[PDB]
Amino acid sequence: KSIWCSPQEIMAADGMPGSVAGVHYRANVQGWTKRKKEGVKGGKAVEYDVMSMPTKEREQVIAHLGLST
């Protein structure tokens, strides 16, 4: 029921341009839900909850998927 996506999918969104940190800049103003995972087979893994982002932001995520699914 919960939804969590890594910054790679988010920064790949045209609505959210800039590298991974560039996305953090926009998320600096709003209190985005963030979680520091112990790294997934890597190191320092970060995820965001799209269900907590404004509805307008939600359209941008679905729109990116609408380009393929």
Image: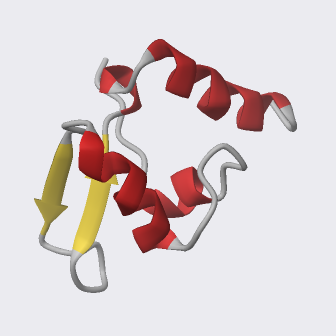
Q: Is residue 14 shown to the viewer in this render?
A: yes
Residue 36 occupies quadrant:
bottom left
Q: Is residue 17 above or below residue 52?
A: below
Where's residue 15, x and y in %? 66, 43
Along the horizontal axis of the image, is 39 left or right of 4? left
* In the image, residue 48 above or below residue 3: below
User: Image quadrant for the C terminus?
Assistant: top right
**Depth check: 62 or 68 in front?**
62
**On the picture, is 51 further left or further right than 36?**
right
Residue sitting at x 25%, y 39%: 32
Residue found at the far bottom of this picture: 42
Residue 14 percent coordinates (x, y): 72, 49
Does residue 5 appear to the left or right of 64 in the view shown? left
Across and down, in percent, residue 16 comes to 59, 50
Which residue is painted at 47% across and 67% down in the image? 22
Query: As rendered, which of 29 and 68 lies closer to the eye?
Result: 29
Closest to the observer, 38 or 34: 34
Q: Is residue 6 visible?
A: no
Q: Residue at x 21, y 78 (%)?
A: 44
Against 52, residue 40 (above or below) is below
Q: Residue at x 27, y 52 (%)?
A: 28
Locate residue 50, reporting x and y percent. 40, 31
